[PDB]
Image (cartoon, coloured by chain):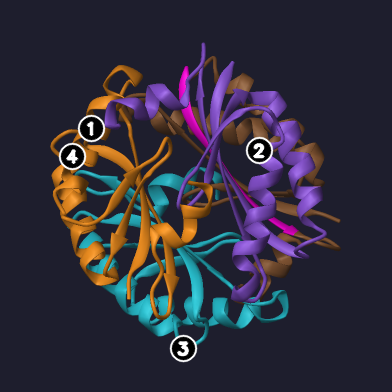
Chain colours: A purple, B orange, C cyan, D brown
């Protein structure tokens, strides 16, 4: 199935670099070719679950060059038969 | 100084009724008078920290009439001197 | 009478080498609340009355700003009408 | 180098079925052979990042037989050179 996965990076860097590491994470996520939405606290991608999990492997390795330590959080909405961003939000927009 | 607080409610109810509990939470959050944004995974409010914490107390009691069991998650971005939704997202918008 | 559990995670925007002092102060502060608590690898879980914990969280945030000008603070609340406890969720495994 | 990954499952089922789905998840996690710790809110594994991400793919598919909709949350502590459960908790135990 197609699912949604919200991704948050919290790097262990001095706060003046915080936003920058996050920008690299967002840019990387945007390269995946999947529908995505940047929010105030996370970035949500919509796509096939196993592909996203593989992309998350690449994202973590990529982020090492910018931050030696970071928290990476995934919030997955897993639904048999699929769930999309629009099904979750369109009613409130 | 403001903070952002992203709020996620995950009720223990059959999938068919998920959307209803969430609707009520979003409706209640919209009543607070604070700037807010509904995302696919959470709803983010911007405002004064202690007031938001008091509003969260009210939200949880309110939700109990719709779901007897739920997960409530707050992701708070706390910055001395304040932080806003725009400072976090506007460059992607 | 009804309790909730609330797991608390602090992630400070400080260099890796200072992460642990902020977290230590957070844990020390949580332990002063008098509530049953358990420190885990990723968070610290308290069991107690919901509104009291929310008020303690207000104090926690103010307290922590001395040690870190910017931090993420995450709460994961298990809310159950009539109450839920740590033991009801983990005793099976311990 | 290891990471720690804290896993939370929140199924969209009635409250009476909730702890059961979670037990199935914990049992499956225990089959991975990795050091793990069950807590009140999540179960933390320590091991190699990419292997854990592949086990998470299997976990989601497995859980589908019990709950057709669920939230699955990963909180990953990622450190250059590795990080362990003991490094994170042993000071407070």
* Mark 1 to mark 4 CA distance (whole Å): 6 Å
Residue count near mark 3 (Cα–Cα under 10 Å), binned few <14, some 14–19, many ≥20: few
Circle 3: element type: loop
Return the residue at label 1.
B23
* Mark 2 to mark 4 CA distance (whole Å): 31 Å
Q: Is residue C16 rendered to the left or right of residue B26? A: right
Task: Indicate the quadrant where residue A9 lies.
Answer: bottom right
Q: Is residue C17 rendered to the left or right of residue D80? A: left
Are the residues tagged 1 and 4 within 8 Å (C-beta)? yes
Can residue C56 be seen in this snapshot? Answer: yes
Chain on which label 2 sits: A
* Mark 3 to mark 1 CA distance (whole Å): 38 Å
- In this rendering, the answer to whether A37 lies above or below A81 is below
For this orientation, the residue located farthest to the top is A81
Q: Position of residue C93 (x, y in %)?
A: 55, 45
Return the residue at label 3.
C66
Q: Give the range drawn in magenta.
A: D68-78
Can residue D58 be seen in this snapshot? Answer: no
Circle 2: element type: helix
Residue located at (21% from left, 49% from top): B60
Return the residue at label 4.
B27
Chain on which label 3 sits: C
Residue count near mark 2 (Cα–Cα under 10 Å), binned few <14, some 14–19, many ≥20: some
- In this rendering, the answer to whether A77 lies above or below C44 is above
Circle 4: element type: helix
Q: Who is closer to the viewer here, D15 or C72?
A: C72
- In this rendering, the answer to whether D81 lies above or below C21 is above
Return the residue at label 2.
A30
Q: Where is residue A88 in the image (x, y as percent from the top left)?
A: 38, 27
Chain on which label 4 sits: B
């Amino acid at each position: 199935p197609k699912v949604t996965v919200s991704i948050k990076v919290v790097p262990a860097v001095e706060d003046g670099r915080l936003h920058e590491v996050i920008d690299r994470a967002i840019e990387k996520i945007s390269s995946w070719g999947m529908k995505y939405e940047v929010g105030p606290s996370n970035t949500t991608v919509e796509g096939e679950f196993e592909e996203i999990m593989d992309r998350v492997k690449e994202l973590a390795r990529y982020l090492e060059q910018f931050a030696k330590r970071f928290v990476l959080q995934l919030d997955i909405d897993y639904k048999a038969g699929g769930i999309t961003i629009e099904e979750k939000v369109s009613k409130y927009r």
